[PDB]
Amino acid sequence: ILLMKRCRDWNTNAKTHTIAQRTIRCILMHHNIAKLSEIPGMVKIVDAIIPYTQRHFTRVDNLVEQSYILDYALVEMDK
Amino acid sequence: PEGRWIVSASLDSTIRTWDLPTGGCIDGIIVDNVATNVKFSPNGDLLAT
Amino acid sequence: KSDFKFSNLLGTVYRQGNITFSDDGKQLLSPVGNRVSVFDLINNKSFTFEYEHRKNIAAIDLNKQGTLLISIDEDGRAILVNFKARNVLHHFNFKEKCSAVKFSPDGRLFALASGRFLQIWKTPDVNKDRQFAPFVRHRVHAGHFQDITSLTWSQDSRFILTTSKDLSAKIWSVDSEEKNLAATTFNGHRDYVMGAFFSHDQEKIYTVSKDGAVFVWEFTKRKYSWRITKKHFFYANQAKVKCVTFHPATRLLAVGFTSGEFRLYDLPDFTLIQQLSMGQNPVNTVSVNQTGEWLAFGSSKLGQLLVYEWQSESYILKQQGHFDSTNSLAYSPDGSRVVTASEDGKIKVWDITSGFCLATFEEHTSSVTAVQFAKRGQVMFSSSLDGTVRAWDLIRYRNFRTFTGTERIQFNCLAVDPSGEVVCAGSLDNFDIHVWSVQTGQLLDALSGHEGPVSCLSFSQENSVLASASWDKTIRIWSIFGRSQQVEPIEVYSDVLALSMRPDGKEVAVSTLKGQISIFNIEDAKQVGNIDCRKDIISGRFNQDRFTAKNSERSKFFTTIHYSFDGMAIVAGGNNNSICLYDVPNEVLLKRFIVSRNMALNGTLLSTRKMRPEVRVTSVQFSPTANAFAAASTEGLLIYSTNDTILFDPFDLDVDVTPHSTVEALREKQFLNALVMAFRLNEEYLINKVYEAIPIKEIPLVASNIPAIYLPRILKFIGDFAIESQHIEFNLIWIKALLSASGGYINEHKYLFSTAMRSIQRFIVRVAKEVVNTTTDNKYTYRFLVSTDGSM
Amino acid sequence: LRIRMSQLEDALMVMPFSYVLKFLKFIDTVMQNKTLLHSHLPLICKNLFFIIKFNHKELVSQKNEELKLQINRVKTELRSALKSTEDDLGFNVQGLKFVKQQWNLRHN
Amino acid sequence: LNDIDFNTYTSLEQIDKELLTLSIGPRSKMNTLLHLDVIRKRSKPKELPFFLQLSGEKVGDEASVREGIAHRRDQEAQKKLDAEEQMNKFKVSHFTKQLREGSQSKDYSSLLATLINFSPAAVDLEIRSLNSFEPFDEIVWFIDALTQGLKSNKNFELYETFMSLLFKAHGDVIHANNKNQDIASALQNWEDVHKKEDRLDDLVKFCMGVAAFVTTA
Amino acid sequence: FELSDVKSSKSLAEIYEDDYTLSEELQKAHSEISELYANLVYKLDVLSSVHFVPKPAETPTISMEDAQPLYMSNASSLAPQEI
Amino acid sequence: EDYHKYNRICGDIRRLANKLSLLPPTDPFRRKHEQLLLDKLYAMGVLTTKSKISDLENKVTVSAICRRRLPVIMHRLKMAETIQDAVKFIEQGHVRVGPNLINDPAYLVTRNMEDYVTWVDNSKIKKTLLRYRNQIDDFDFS
Amino acid sequence: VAPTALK
């Protein structure tokens, strides 16, 4: 619970969301996901992570989206 | 009115419908009396001769 | 250079009369004032019939075959139309107010409720050629002494039940020989009998009265005679029964009360299936589906229409039209959606494809005057006489910010920076253009300099100049952005009512009271062209007029104008019956449109105001798709489109060019010649044939070698085709091939391909992106369920 | 990193092409060091897109075959980095909502 | 050549087998299916004794107040009564059949046809009605049917959303028994097919980037 | 505030009975003002309107118009900062 | 001359104010509808100057409503000799209130629209006026 | 049976 209190505070800032997500990834990958739910207060911590995670997901996907400006460069000058 | 068809009348007492995209006659008629004039209606549903 | 044609009417789904479901049950026929609207419930699509009545519509029905539809107005003048081909067949005048019309369940005859008289008429055969006098009468029945409420046919097409203001229900036999079978009058009801129905076996007869009494009739001994064995009563405290319908197959009784609530019952047990309220206004009409699973209800006062899947208690269709006239309209930048603004003060967001209202906004207290989108399209802005300007997010559908003047200035026009950071509005009482910051909501400053009231505003999409006009007989160009502020006033011959802005942002067009559309050069501030409008406009002498229309000067100007996105045409309208489309470079009239042909509307042909509705066009704009343009009017949002494209408009054609030759090229595998040849014919079906016949391996080759002149056409063709096509990834290859091969050219000429690129982006963002989102989320849903540990 | 963001776009805009070619060489060596890339990926991505957008015509004209290889390599490693963070994000959120649903079902 | 003779042409059902194609129907169907739950929630309609019992300050007994001395289940009981009244008010599958046969013949084509025909309200009930007891035959069968559908490369949007409702309705059931071979094997088969269907992202996400760059700069 | 000086119609059982069961009386005057205004604005508008002005307008009710799309979920309408 | 309708408006204004005066002074709802009422009455011009609710009780009169009638305004504005002549000009369609033509004598001008009541451009009588001054312009069609 | 019955 103490660790998840941090990662929530870490996630909201775009400059630091990268670290928090991997910590979330490890915990879901190294614990019984059922057990995590019974922990009191966890779900309300879980509540705040979701909206910010989606915003960062819309981001990055857009940074990905801009990336084929470079294949537009490759294919064009290849001509 | 659609610009897709032309219908003409001639002294041989016939009315021929021509399909412009393919440039061929699609229908033919024989009138007892030679049709002096031929006019489509603005809507295209009607034809006056 | 395209022929527009009326397609559908948004903003209104029901006005009055009876609504009938299609025999297939997948389409609903709803009367809308002077016209009839068709909604495809399954396909989530709608259209409005082009044919129009002299007066407001009264009653309709569709034959089971789905081929013949008869429409009768309030004067009894009937229009027979082929449902499949959407064309009028015959006009007949029954010379009396027809309350109800219903085809026979054989389809050979149709009954007409005419006063206290029942008319039966033989149905013309659609297969036969156009007959001059196809209507021949089978029989005239005169049993009732007052008006007939409604009539019901026997499932075997042999008997007709008629309910009238007699407080009685009377039956007939369609066959003269069978008169003795059914020649009885039913009595007992203490109020007006509205609807009489047969059971599935037809043994029993159910009659309903306005007081809310249901009487069940059987043929039994006391030697046999009809009698009321069972009686059921609706115990509405004050609500009167307004419309009733019955489905014998499922024994469903749907009743609509004047209080605005409808009740579903099972006969003969009278089990109250469900009871809901549509509001406080009467339920005018009710209908049942052929299966009996969908019920359609209609309230005339608010134009409310709803289709109810009472089995699942779900809403198939749920729409309410504007109570007032639509004052303004605005398309989304992509053109997927349109927003309509009404004098009530409520905004409504509409989807072009579905033709349905996604949401309504009621925050504005008074009438909303103008609506516009930002260049992004995520945000929409609106102004109202209540003294506020409100900014709306359309992704989340919420009012995130509101602006207002210091002293509650009434606003009439609005304009938005393409950057989406400045909003300006004009008023008819201050002569100042208020400026607000979108980000902050603070009044940046008030632009002053107008010697008259500001009538209109617009920000240049590219350069970001602001051009404002007034009744001041002058136009001022504002360079608000930058360290220094400059204003360039231009004089005009008369008061300026409307203004349009060229998308390039180099020219501005303005409509004046003289009936002149004057085009100026923004950079040079010099007039470049003018168009006369006084003579083209059509204005009908009002019924209250005591002076002639030709001498009339009430309206021979255009109150609204707008460019075409191509930039070669202007669409204009005013408080008249005419919408005129012009060609700017040549200054000629392309075509004129008649807004309405309803004789009830005033202009189509001492303390009390002689005051009735008038035909007028509040606003007009082009669709960004460059295929349609919508005009806001009193009746609603009219949309005219070129989608039919049944015209033959060949481009650079030659004798060698022929549909058969194009097919031969495909068989000989000359795809480029076959593809190029297709556009020269410019026939959509041939282009489709060539487009889908090209193998994927050869797509990059043909795309690279396409001539430049045909590139804008093919790019447009793919965009409109791909939006509704199923070959998603095939189109994606085609778009990829064209852009990769001809990308540099499009950059050099952005404006030439501006509309074509936009239609491509609409397909990619609205449907293609949605698929990958449903694709990618499952991919991660897969990885979680497999990777992480299972529950204890 | 020291350059303020608001002046950054103008800083790239004033920048001549001959230095932009140098700046492409800079990214490639930074991209070779994987650790530094992920620490400052979002800032690097925005700068690269702006430069290429702002010098697209200059870029296409150049006939340096080596310049192909520089643009090709930066692409492949950039995609892995962006995809990696995206995959981690999509991975977390999807399971993250799954936990919410399970807790609801237990208490409902 | 009859189509030419009538100046008409109908688009092919599928240009080529390898080529992904969407369903022949409205594109709002996928949106309706995915969020059908909130459609249901949002569409729901809008909703003395003789021995009167008071005490405390208002009855003037401030001493009781100063000295410190000072129904939801009843609503819950009533809600039960309202439900009980409802059942007495009314005093009155093809899907599951084909699913068993499709497993028997290893051919879900007849099944897949009915899924497309079903209304969205019909769709969600059938997915939710799949049994969730061991050995989970129907769920394993359902994924095989969809796995066959994705191979067809036809009706791509519909098959994708079908599993989302499966996971939405039976994600916990699948997860709790992830280690079961039958679930794992069929589940593994689906990824093999679905993994191939990622090229479409490349194309769609490709044509946006160049289009965004082309229109802008 | 004013204190009545005439005998109360309500008996002590009744006054307390009222306590057993911001103000409905205030909320009735709340509406009665609105309809007077709604009727007044209509009349004054038609005199001053150049064009047409239409006259302004248990059981479960169907909300015939909605402020938001059905498919959109309430949680999706809240910004991350709000959460 | 009948003023039953105007009397109904004035009485309704008094009734609305009386019902307002019944409501608590501290109620925010009462205050705004009072101010909204005073605003619209000012907007129409029947209130020449911004006033209080007490003034709105008595200052409102039939004559004030009659004063704002379009033919009356022209009479003060000197377009017509008499109210009957003004009505005839309104009747014949020579009078224009801003962007639109008014043929109804019963119409009243709001305060803002007063400044723009003017005769239609091609009215024959304007040609007389500019002819008298000898300032007729055929180019301006008037 | 009723005279109005089917058949």
Image (tube, rainbow, N blue to C red):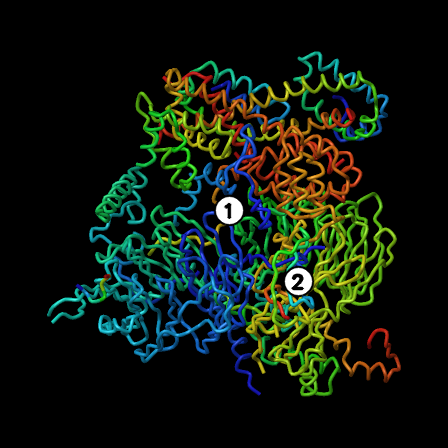
Report x, y in % for residue G44. Answer: 63, 70
Residue C542's quadrant in the figure? bottom right
The amino acid marked with disc number 2 is: Val
The residue lying toward the viewer, choosing from D80 and G135, is D80
On the image, numbered disc 1 is attached to which residue?
Answer: F68
Q: Against D65, is C282 above or below?
A: below
On the image, numbered disc 2 is attached to which residue?
Answer: B7
Q: Is residue C718 left or right of residue C534?
A: left
Residue B46, label in figure: none
Write the residue at 38% across / 60% down.
C286
Report x, y in % for residue C665. Answer: 68, 38
Alpha carbon separation for disc pair 1 and 2: 57 Å
Residue C302 shows up from this direction:
no
Dot 2: element = strand
Q: Against C458, is G98 above or below?
A: below
Report x, y in % for residue G91. Answer: 66, 83
Q: Against C28, is G73 above or below?
A: below
The amino acid marked with disc number 1 is: Gln
Write the residue at 39% across / 24% down.
E172
Q: Against C737, is E59 above or below?
A: below
